[PDB]
Amino acid sequence: QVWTPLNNKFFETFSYLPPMTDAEISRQVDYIVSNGWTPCLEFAGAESAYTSNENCVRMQNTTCLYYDNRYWTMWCTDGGQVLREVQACRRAFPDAYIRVVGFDPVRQVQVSGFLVNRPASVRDYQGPSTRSV
Amino acid sequence: LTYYTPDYQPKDTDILAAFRMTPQPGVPPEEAGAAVAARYKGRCYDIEPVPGEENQYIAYIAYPLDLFEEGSVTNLFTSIVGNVFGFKALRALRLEDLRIPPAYVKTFQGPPHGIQVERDKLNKYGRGLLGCTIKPKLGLSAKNYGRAVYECLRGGLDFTKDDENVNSQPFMRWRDRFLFVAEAIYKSQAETGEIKGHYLNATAATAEEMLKRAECAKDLGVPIIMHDYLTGGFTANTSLAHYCRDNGLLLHIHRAMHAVIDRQRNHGIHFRVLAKALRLSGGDHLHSGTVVGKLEGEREVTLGFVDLMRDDYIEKDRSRGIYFTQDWVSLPGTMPVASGGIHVWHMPALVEIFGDDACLQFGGGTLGHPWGNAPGAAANRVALEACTQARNEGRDLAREGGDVIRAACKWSPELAAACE
Amino acid sequence: LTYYTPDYQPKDTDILAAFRMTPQPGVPPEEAGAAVAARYKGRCYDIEPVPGEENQYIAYIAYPLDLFEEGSVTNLFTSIVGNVFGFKALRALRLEDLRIPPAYVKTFQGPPHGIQVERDKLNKYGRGLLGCTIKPKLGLSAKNYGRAVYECLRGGLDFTKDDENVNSQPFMRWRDRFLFVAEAIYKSQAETGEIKGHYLNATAATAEEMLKRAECAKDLGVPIIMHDYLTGGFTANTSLAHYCRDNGLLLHIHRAMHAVIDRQRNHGIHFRVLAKALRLSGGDHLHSGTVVGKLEGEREVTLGFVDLMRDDYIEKDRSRGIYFTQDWVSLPGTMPVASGGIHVWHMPALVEIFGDDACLQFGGGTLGHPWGNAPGAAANRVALEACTQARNEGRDLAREGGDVIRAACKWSPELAAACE
Amino acid sequence: DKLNKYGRGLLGCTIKPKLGLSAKNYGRAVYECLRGGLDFTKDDENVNSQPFMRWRDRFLFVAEAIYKSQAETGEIKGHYLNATAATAEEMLKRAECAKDLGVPIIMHDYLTGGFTANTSLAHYCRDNGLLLHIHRAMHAVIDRQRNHGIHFRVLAKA
Amino acid sequence: LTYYTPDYQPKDTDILAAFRMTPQPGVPPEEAGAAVAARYKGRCYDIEPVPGEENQYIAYIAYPLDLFEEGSVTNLFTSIVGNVFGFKALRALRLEDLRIPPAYVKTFQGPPHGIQVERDKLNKYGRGLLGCTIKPKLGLSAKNYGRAVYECLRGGLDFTKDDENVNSQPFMRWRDRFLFVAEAIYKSQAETGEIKGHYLNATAATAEEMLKRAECAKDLGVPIIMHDYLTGGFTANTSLAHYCRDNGLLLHIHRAMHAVIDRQRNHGIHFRVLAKALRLSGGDHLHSGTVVGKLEGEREVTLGFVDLMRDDYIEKDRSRGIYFTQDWVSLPGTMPVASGGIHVWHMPALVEIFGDDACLQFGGGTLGHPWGNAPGAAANRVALEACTQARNEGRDLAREGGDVIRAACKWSPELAAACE
């Protein structure tokens, strides 16, 4: 079989697994909470979801390690609350990818980041069986 | 003995070494420790016999901080192990550990970015990184090398790397390879939407040539380069690490020629000291182990030097080979890179042993997947993500790795052709 | 075995290695040689058992010339001994010799000046050179270091040198030492009328700092600098050697950390390979032996690597450890430097063993002469000149060294206080 | 004229927490505050270059945040990047990085860095078209007591 | 004769020359060879008479490798043919061939990219390259020159080139031409989707000006430049080739003033020696022949120097003028460029003679197509592709070239107006 290079976009962690269900998202959020970390939600439409070099035109010397759309837009006690917020974000922005992020409150660093929602309207991604043709 | 002072209390600024030495018969251990030790004099303050080996002692030496040049791994190695392995009074001598006082650590820049800055720059969290060594090792043209890089990266791999002996040869000059690899990296980035990279080998004959190759990598905008620090030298490595910090480049470190110094148990320098010297000199990644069949070497020793090269504060643990408490005073950590034959069903073991802050390298070049390079990379990525997800759910990977692999294979056609 | 080809005839451009390997029991020697060997493939073309050692063989490997980067000792060592000492199938492995084909040799600059250009620049002919290591090793201020240098050089010594661990410390910064040593060198030159020099240590943390120290030495007009190539690295050494050729500076090379790689007979890289790598990378002098009591190590082995690092054409001689004929195609030779406890009555032996093309180093700092540093230097110079004159007359030094020393002492008051 | 903002005061925020935040999280906070409608954000006065957040990582992440907020809102945005450093060479290098990123404005502590360093930075900013925000750290040590010291108005004129 | 040694066996590192000499009557051939030959002495080791010419001999001279400066074609030509064509004892003298030992070859960088790297960079495989010389030769403004370049490239030509005498004149300054040609190249690339190029003439009065023109070409991002090596000089050429390797630029070489040295059979230097000197100095393309009517010159001689400038290993073949076996030890090959009146029906002959690794140049400026420059370029491209396809099918081009051309013309309206 051949890995398809057409409409096969991916979003880093857990993006190569089948779309996670509510129970799986809940278990991941519980894992984040268990470690002592804070979960939050990021979202972006299809125009600002993938990495790009749009602003590299303004730079000189080098553009090493600079990529656009690394930041998404921010949307935290347990899995159920984060799941409710996931549904709320889905209703508010149906054409936007949702990403669950984790933040270590002591080190003040991001420790987690996995996609939990892919807009049905957008078709820039494949499915577990359509990834190979 | 003016140089054996068992009542001496080491200062907070002393550099401490733990030597495993076997003196010649008739030489008392105190005399041998005094010799190794011999205001600016190194002194043996502690000697303990090794329980299990005949005529084997651990000698603890304290060096004043004024003895060394600030921020110079070269000087540190010249002072500590310059001419001490040639003493006739010692049948065998092995440096086991070093204690770098914070006062000395603060004089070093350290790794250019570290693990957390690397994760933030690459926007990859919660999982180990994946890499492949482009194979065949040599003979491939820059165009074909770039084609292989693009094929492996588009599958889902986060990194690819040049072979350790690929610097600049008649078959493939370095600038052609850099250009074709840059095109491949950018194509794979556009196709998958994830940030990709390739460990471009900057190891060269002269520091000027090495800096020129780093400069070309910086001008292409590519993320990361590679260096052979034990063959290029600490002086060349430190220059490259300073350059990478200045210009925002990641630095992968390969430990070529390491077994010539850290293989024999009785003679040489233990890899943990070389790992601490690398972290001081600078490196974002450091090839730290081989997985032939399984992770080779005592697990505790591996865990010890992985913690020594990763954490900020490592307490003394003789079980794992930590002879001294090591405070890193906020020096950036180095990401360990486990390479070799990482088979798909062996991923759960390595994910359990290393965790998320490591790079698993398929130095075998994969190619074992009947479909191609890209599906093989996808299978590996699927397996790693499935193992990580299972571990996050509370599963015991060492007991359910096969079950997790099978369950992932049930829905992954690419992994199905890999699991067979 | 695709990699064991006993009928293969090595090409005139192949790089040849002679490995002394002890395979694990049950592993045939042919299989082990095939593994070490494994168009661009290294191949084992010859295996000979070691007569005198059990399960010990010499494996001859042929590498194509296209495998290596032109003028890069770093790449050569990465390719040959990068990851081969870590093979589990080998109980022990030792690289004994290398054959550098002329085609490869011509891609290297080599030593900046060589022996003959050194003699012409220093205007010293027909005798060995003399040097001292300023002692105490550390703690001395730049002013006092310069005073010691001037006192030792005015006596008749041709060179002095910084201690191997003296680079730049709180007690003595490097630029102060360079300035005071320059004043001392010029004072001793004016006083004696002979050209003097001091091995200024340029070994530093970064290549930039090392080049800055070399630049300061060039701006002072002093003749020679020093480098630690096994700790600084081949990349740093090659940069320094290119700089020294460009700016007309001599380069003394110290082999710090050598015993960590060339001490054990079963594992490591023999010093002769490190000496050939140094000659390729560049160095006018290379500390080549210690004289504790007497010249240590098998004489034939020492003579072998001295000839390998000095002569232009060395024929294969297994008695002296030459496993391959080495053609240097007019590459400048490196002057061997024998250091350690060179006592006055031991000068005839070393003059006989080394001849005129060597530097005898009093690394003990002398100080054994009751009168002072300067008369001790004079005594040494008188002894060396008397031994050379006796050898030129047809005397057998190994049999009449004591007679020659006594006869010189009969007229030398300085040597009289030294001979006691 | 450069910022195309007329008829109103400008608005700025100091990214908080003061210290401990990673360059990524600092950039995230900058982007979140700027996208709301703020014209400027600024580094904390004591944020120059620390083990927790090196200066070049912060400059890069802040540049990405500034450009994202500009694209989202359509208004020109900026962040007072702290160029205050130990040596004039390091300070000019940080200003040079800001110039190479195309970001609008940098910051300096003139009473702690010194007038000599400030004048060099101001000449550089005029030469390269960069705005310069000045923070008066250590001012109360000289302009607080009514009987002794130098009144702030003299420091403002200087 | 101390310089005629018929029993001498040339070394593997000797530089060998084969001189065709006609001595004055009364001078024996041995004496004349001894004179040309006259540890560092050149020696005549072989003399063979020419069967077919009266008083004509081939003299073989062996020069030691130590005689020449590493990587210097200038020195090689100064040593070999500096002052030997002015000997009164020789009626005529002609250097026929040179043997460059691998040891010497390794000291040269060679062509910046070579044939295979060129093909990979341009992404063109399996066919010869096509070029045109913009005509009229002179008088055209930079704007009109660019217009002609764009019109010829959009038709399907891979390259265009400046006239040999077009460097920088009042009618067309060089920077205006570079800018307009860059615009034309980019327009043609966007229109056709194939990578295009134009041989920009960097030949200038001073090396500084030549490097400035190369720098402008590099700043425009254009692929290739041109140089006149026999008029600019080997020193200027070697500088340009090093620059092109450093900055990733292709280098086309034009052999202006060649007939002044390689035309007469009795006196001068044969073009094959100039081609080997160019390959050593550096050049990706080398104008190698003219096709006035048909490929001019003995086919075997042309094939010989084409193989000498293309292949890695050329065995001695006196039938094709190869007097010595030439090992290139992986030096990049040079692409031969056949220029002149390449008419459409003459394409099969040149495709058969040269193969795919050559550039056919329409130095006549085409313009013979009644429709325009672009359709004429298309006709040429169609003819070349049809001939290549026929050759790949097993057709005999020398016998079916007309049939293939007619068959291609049956479906190509552009070729129909060209075939008439």
Image (cartoon, coloured by chain):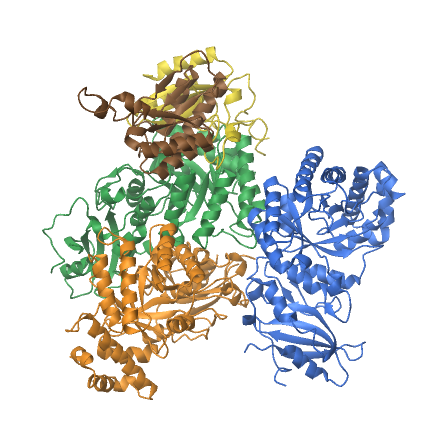
Chain colours: A yellow, B green, C orange, D brown, E blue
Which residue is located at x 50 percent, y 23 percent?
A: A49
Can residue C93 be seen at all in this image of the molecule? yes
In the displayed structure image, the side of residue B331 where residue D148 appears, left or right: left
Q: Give the image quarter of residue E323.
A: bottom right
Residue closer to the observer: E274 or C158: C158
Q: Where residue D73 sits in the image (x, y, percent)? A: 48, 16
Residue C200 image point, x, y percent: 31, 61
Q: Quadrant of residue E289?
A: bottom right
**Image quarter of residue B119:** top left
Q: Nearer the viewer, residue B376 or B238?
A: B238
Left or right: where does residue E184 sit relative to residue B249?
right
User: Residue E114, relative to residue A68: is it above or below?
Assistant: below
From what the image shows, is residue B262 above or below residue E383?
Answer: below
Question: Which one is nearer the viewer's eye here, D41 or B82?
Answer: D41
What is the quadrant of the C terminus of chain C in the image? bottom left
Q: Nearer the viewer, residue B110 or D91?
A: D91
Q: Residue at x 57, y 31 (%)?
A: A132
Relative image position of residue C69 (x, y in whole percent): 50, 56
- Taking the spot 45% from the left edge, 49% from the top edge, the residue there is B210
Which residue, as the protein is rendered here, is positioned at the far bottom?
C394
On the image, the x and y values in percent for residue B178 come to 53, 44
Count of marks overlaid on the render: 0
Residue at the extreme right of the image, as rendered: E420
Residue C131 shows up from this direction: no
Residue B321 position (above or below residue D29):
below
Q: Is residue B57 left or right of residue B296?
A: left
